[PDB]
Amino acid sequence: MRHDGRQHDELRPITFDLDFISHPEGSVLITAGNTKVICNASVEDRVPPFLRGGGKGWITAEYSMLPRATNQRTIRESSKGKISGRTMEIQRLIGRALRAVVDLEKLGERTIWIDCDVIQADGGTRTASITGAFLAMAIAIGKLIKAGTIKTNPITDFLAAISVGIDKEQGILLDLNYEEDSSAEVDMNVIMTGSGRFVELQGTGEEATFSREDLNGLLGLAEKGIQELIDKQKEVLGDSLP
Amino acid sequence: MRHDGRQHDELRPITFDLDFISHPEGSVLITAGNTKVICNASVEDRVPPFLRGGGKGWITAEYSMLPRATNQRTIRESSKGKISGRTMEIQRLIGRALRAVVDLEKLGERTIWIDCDVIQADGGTRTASITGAFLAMAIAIGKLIKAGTIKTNPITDFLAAISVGIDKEQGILLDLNYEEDSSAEVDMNVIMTGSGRFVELQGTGEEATFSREDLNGLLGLAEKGIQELIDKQKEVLGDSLP
Amino acid sequence: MRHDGRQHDELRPITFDLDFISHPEGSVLITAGNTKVICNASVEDRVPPFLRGGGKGWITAEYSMLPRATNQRTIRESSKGKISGRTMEIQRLIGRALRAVVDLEKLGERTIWIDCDVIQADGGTRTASITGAFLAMAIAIGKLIKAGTIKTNPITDFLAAISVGIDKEQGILLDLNYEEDSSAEVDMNVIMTGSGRFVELQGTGEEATFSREDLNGLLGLAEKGIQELIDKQKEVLGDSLP
Amino acid sequence: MRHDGRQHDELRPITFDLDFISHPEGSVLITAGNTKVICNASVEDRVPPFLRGGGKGWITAEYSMLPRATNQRTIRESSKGKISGRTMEIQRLIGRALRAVVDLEKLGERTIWIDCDVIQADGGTRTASITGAFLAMAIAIGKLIKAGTIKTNPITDFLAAISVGIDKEQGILLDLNYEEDSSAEVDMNVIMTGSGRFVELQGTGEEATFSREDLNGLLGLAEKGIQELIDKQKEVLGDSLP
Amino acid sequence: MRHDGRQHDELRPITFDLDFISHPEGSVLITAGNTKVICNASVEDRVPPFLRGGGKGWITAEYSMLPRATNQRTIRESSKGKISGRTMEIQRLIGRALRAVVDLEKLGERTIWIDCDVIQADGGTRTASITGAFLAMAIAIGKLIKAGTIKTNPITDFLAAISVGIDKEQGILLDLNYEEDSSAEVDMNVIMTGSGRFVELQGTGEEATFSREDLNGLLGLAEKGIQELIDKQKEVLGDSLP
Amino acid sequence: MRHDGRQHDELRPITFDLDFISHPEGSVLITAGNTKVICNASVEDRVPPFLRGGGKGWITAEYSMLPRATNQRTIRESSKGKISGRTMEIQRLIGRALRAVVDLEKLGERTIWIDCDVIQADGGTRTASITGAFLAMAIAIGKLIKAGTIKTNPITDFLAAISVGIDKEQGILLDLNYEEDSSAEVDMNVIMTGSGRFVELQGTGEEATFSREDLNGLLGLAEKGIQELIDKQKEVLGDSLP
């Protein structure tokens, strides 16, 4: 059916290499098929202008794609006097997402920096980033508990995301890759929690348009994949967090 | 209930001033409550690099917000050596949307430029722009038919959009304004066709998160509003297009 | 004689729509023939680096021309990594002009932002902008008096401007439009006060060159038109300012 | 009367060092009192987008002021992510001016680059630049004739400029310097041809305003000075151009 | 002695993970202590303007440092409208270096892109990059031979680099890290070949200054370390290149 | 032997015109053969962020090359939205160098701005700049002593630099020019003090590579030239500094 040889509702092989990079408090290298992203979580007692003594913590994220992470070498973002739209659109998405499952108050007035740097791109880097950004943030926060830097665990749920779409001649597809995301008529990112609720939904029909029926199809497929992801997420994380 | 004094499922008053600006082939000034956007459609026999002799036409759009279109004067985008993220995120959305209802082949190898410049902002400028950008594009194409510059009408459907959201203490709301969009927990733009199908769906829960139930609520409300919009769209357009 | 069907010393029809845009303290939509400019005045207690506690106020202005405001769609200035020369040359002119008739000391240490955004261009947008920028600034300051935010009226005179030129086969022309400004041998912007004095004079002979005689001809014509403008300016403003 | 010890209608001492810098086709170091500008003319067979095969040549100019060319060290323009307004306003003025006395057609489809870099500033750098930019351009074109790269001499006249103004307690002054231009009520740049015609007139009353009488005064003084300049211009240029 | 617990002439532990990233023809992840750099080599039949049909190949390189690769999160280079000096200074160094050991003629008219992206920085990233950039380039070229895309092996030698310096109270140090490079009086990068010759020497005494004696000390130490590096380089590369 | 007709170990004729430009505290026009650089030193009681009340002074430098300072007109750096690499690489070098011979503490909490603007380039502009930048800085500081603005002389040594290299068929060459630096196999800048110590060493073998023997050759030649430079430096400076 599909050129990977996977069923329409099958995720790509996932691997989670923990503590990939020494320095960061939380570091995970998520591999989803050929998509590889380095997710690092860094803590730092400090907050932007509007959180002064608010006893509320923050979570921001930066996302980049190495020039030859893609099939064709894309111009380094630094070369251009500005950060591209995608990077912009994506960085906010990752931060917005992670915050939805963390008690910013219980975290303290500290700030968590999430750096998602894609070293190999083959579709679904946006979502793959969120999935691994969580694990990393968890580990960073998990070991923040140990050293007694916070008394309670701020994480109020598991988080994960996955792309899904419709291919003119194959229908619904779970977890697209560059090939698929490139020719699909309806691209669609879905981000949920362990408790099966939605954090964010972003669907766009570039070629054609979808119906209430199509939608419910994609949502159902995505939900299935995300649960599959959160499981793998639970075993791996295991002890790092109570 | 709401400070406009409108019901939970009532649109703001809409007005369509046609031919607002002489010069452009298509020009419409859409007014949605206090939101006012100037939508101009310009034709131009030419295409980007990848449409050379492809017999395929294009549709691109640029969106700007005059500095004091907002309650607080925002720095002119030109002043900054770069175009902001929103503008970026929005310009693509408008173009992507319009293309979903136009047979780029039947249009020819010409290019349609859509300029949506907001002169007064009070919420839902993104959607209001798409709604009026259509009308303008229709008129431009409509009169392109007359002069026999194309033999068949490329427009394959009507297009419109509308914001919808959830207010902590009021629930579902159709067509938010700046105050509402500002305090809503779940923002959500919806773009559909006359045939009741989806072109794009963008929903984000900044404060909290939504459920499959909430979603189906919003979608249902949006759908209702959009149909209401396409009607007004049909009478006004009337003859300009066959 | 002239295609508008107007005499060499006749101004184009002028209209002043006050309070066009809700948000700004001062907002005027000046229409001069087919030239339409949105002039907004915004107050803001603050000053650049060199006015710290100087008890002196400031007045700066930004000018833009919507992409399809012109007969041919010009590339959006934001698209280019820089602001064009004209815009530059013009923004400074408007600010310089307005300041020449305002007691920056009596104004206070606040700052007035003038945004002149041309929505339809057909010649003399530079001057039309100044003419309307004044009215807007007047209204903003006028209502700044009421609320007792300043004790005395800073405006020390009326201000207005108008283009004038020489056409190879028609001679002196008052208030050119795109067609005329385009083929005239001698373009020339003139900015004066109610008291009949000059604030700025900018004359350039692109094709040929002019003589002391020609000059005195243009200046005399311009002066006539400007007085005509300041009258219309007086009735309209009327009460908004003491 | 004046600190320099010069009469109201006396120019500052002028010197023209030809071929100052080896590399450029035309190079002149103009010294006007304490104002020193390096004017270089560079030829280059090529034209911008709109002169392709038009058989029409171009003339553009860039102007800069070395950081400590002024009494106080001004921030390098490169340091700022943008070119200042003055530089902008001035670069265009120089190019516009030179073009007014050159048959762009007879020049060919080549392009002349004029670089006016001020190494010591003490007033009237804008005008001094034009005066010397001409000489340089003349020499470049003059020796372009010799090598038979063009058959006819494109220069259709001599060009020069000079500042003039009014001092509250001294009246009309010819060729101001930094201290005079700084306290004058009416600044005013005048650019003319050998044939005594005007190319550009730029007058501004910052403090006060001027009358038709004042104007005719300044114009008359400027004209006198410019003729004086074109003479010095004729002997020096001498043979370099037929 | 030193905080790593290593002798003054001991290198940090080095590891070479080959084929780290699938996509690039050559991909190596060099780890030097805590410094980790992803070195990717990409081939591409094409050359800049001045190598058209010259039968000469090229080698260019881009270098970046992920925002939180450093102990403190540095602003993304893309965020700034420009690429920093270091990046500039470094990118050229890497390219210049690699070219010194490759017969650009035997390579063909193709172009090799080297992307050195540092994912974890702890000193000597500049040099570590060159050392790994070679290995990657070797592999890319090595497998270019196999597929018979070139008949002869262009690499004319092995290349490697290493930092060295002087610490106020410890003397000569081989292979500094962030801590050491930060407090050393004399920083100094050295790049040599297998044949023990110099390709580039860059030494700078920020605090103090060095003597002919000091220099010969550093050079001798560096040379020792580099040879050590080229060995590890030989075994790892092993067969990938004849 | 060499086109100039100078021996392999002969410097180009050097001239030092003091007080070239009135305004700056220190101003020197260094001429090395055909290379001409304007070196200006400007004092300014103030320091960047990290020197607040530190009683430590600073020294920064900016370097530019006028567009037609070179044989071919290079694009103005301002035209490009960024400062080139060379300029970057060089500006830092000059500042770094000068600081190595000045007791920043004895200087005070003031800041010295060095502007090296090349008006005619023919090789060795980088070094020529440092050589003259010193003289200028000396004079600025020298006359800072007189007016008793500082009690002790901060300059702890003389500074100078010179390029040196190897020509495929001529060997070692002292003080290259554009032609020589262009075809040399080994370029190499050397910066030393009067006390014969090294401040910075930058050597690069673009074509080939050099050996310990070659190196010691160049270093020995450079050292010879630099001493020759510091002498000329001593007489000229003479009294300006104790």
Image (cartoon, coloured by chain):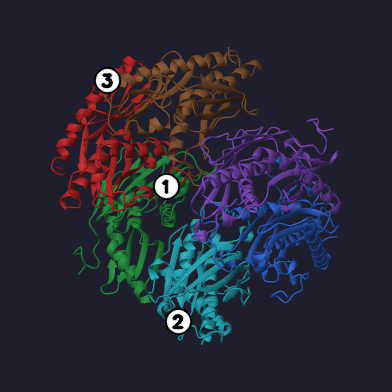
Chain colours: A cyan, B green, C red, D brown, E blue, F purple
In the rendered structure, which amino acid carries the disc numbered 1? Ser
Secondary structure beneath label 1: loop
Secondary structure beneath label 2: loop
Identify the mark at residue A154; answer none if there is no mark.
Answer: 2
Judge if badges 1 and 3 mark residues of a common chain: no
Residue, disc 1: B78
Judge if badges 2 and 3 mark residues of a common chain: no
Q: Is residue B30 left or right of residue C146?
A: right
Q: CA distance from mark 2 to mark 1?
A: 42 Å
Q: CA distance from mark 1 to mark 3?
A: 42 Å
In the rendered structure, which amino acid carries the disc numbered 2? Pro
Residue, disc 3: D213
Tell me, yes or no, whether the two marked residues, 1 and 3, touch with CB atoms within 8 Å: no
Query: Percent from the top left, x then y, of residue B220?
Result: 32, 68
Chain letter belonging to callout 3: D
Out of A178 and F133, give the one closest to the viewer: F133
Secondary structure beneath label 3: helix
Residue occupying the point 56% across, 84% down: A240
Is any part of residue D190 visible from this angle?
A: yes
